[PDB]
Image (cartoon, coloured by chain):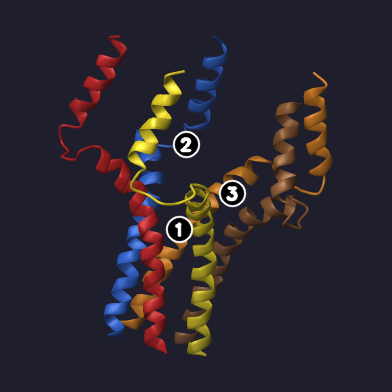
Chain colours: A orange, B blue, C red, D yellow, E brown
């Protein structure tokens, strides 16, 4: 291999400045964006309910 | 195979905390986003019609 | 290839509840989204011109 | 080839109704969207500065 | 190789009109968009707090 031990070692070396179970990093970026769309929606609705 | 029975079994094992015909999960994330764009549009128009 | 006649027949069977030249279905989803971005833009500008 | 002369000829045939150096078509769709996000941002800020 | 020296040389040739450590270019486009979603959110909230 040498090619993998080099790539995996390159990450653990540049990722020693983070603290997440990985899975949360990926799930959060995607789940977040979709969560944002729904958040901005319920938001605009609030503002409207106030103008009534 | 062993490689598939391992991947399919890994999902049914981590997906036992869900209840959807799969198809709705995929169709909803994509159909939803597009639905959001149209929803936010008809929304801004409403607010405008009120400022007139 | 029995494999194609099975896939093409599966669509014409589940698509008998639609009426579009196909091409409009694909062109509309993509052209629409891009059209939405430009629509929401000219929109925000309108609202602003009104607050002036 | 015959496969390429057929695909390239199919485009120049259906693209004879356009006038762009190609590069602008691709760069514009992507650069535009990103430009839109920044445009909508500076926009909301304007409206706010007016409500103050 | 001749194929790589040709692609890498084609970039450094068309990128001599930029000044960024590369990494910031990629990290900024993605980090920016996500930053925008959060920015627009805290924004709508501000406006609301003002209508109260």
Give the class, few, some or many, for how many residues have Cα within 10 Å of label 1's Cα (few <14, many ≥20).
some
Point out the tag, 1 or 3, that comes first from the N-terminus.
3
Which residue occupies the foreground of this view, D13 or A43? D13
Would you name the residue on which mark 1 appears?
A37
Q: Nearer the viewer, mark 2 or mark 3?
A: 3
Which residue is painted at 49% across and 74% down in the image?
E44
Find residue A28 and name its label.
3
Residue B12: x %, y % from top left: 48, 26
C-alpha span from label 2 to label 1: 24 Å
Which residue is painted at 62% across and 53% down in the image?
E30
Is B33 left, or right, of E35 in this rendering? left
Q: Chain of mark 2?
A: B
Seen in the picture, residue B27 relative to B50 is either above or below; the reply is: above
Which residue occupies the foreground of this view, A5 or A48? A5
Dots 2, 3 in contact, CB < 8 A: no
Q: Quadrant of residue A23?
A: top right
- SS of the residue under disc 2: loop
Which residue occupies the foreground of this view, B39 or D6? D6
- SS of the residue under disc 3: helix
- Disc tally is 3
Q: Chain of mark 3?
A: A
Is A3 left, or right, of B8 in this rendering? right
Residue B10: x %, y % from top left: 54, 24
Same-chain status of marks 1 and 3: yes
Q: Chain of mark 1?
A: A
Would you name the residue on which mark 2 appears?
B17
Is B20 left, or right, of E49 in this rendering? left
Give the class, few, some or many, for how many residues have Cα within 10 Å of label 3's Cα (few <14, many ≥20).
few
Q: Nearer the viewer, mark 1 or mark 3?
A: 1
Residue A11: x %, y % from top left: 78, 38
- SS of the residue under disc 1: helix
C-alpha span from label 1 to label 3: 14 Å
């Amino acid at each position: 291999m040498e090619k993998v031990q080099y790539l995996t070692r390159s990450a653990i070396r540049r990722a020693s400045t983070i603290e997440m179970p990985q899975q949360a990093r990926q799930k959060l970026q995607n789940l977040f964006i979709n969560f944002c769309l729904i958040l901005i929606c319920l938001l605009l609705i609030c503002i409207i309910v106030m103008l009534l």
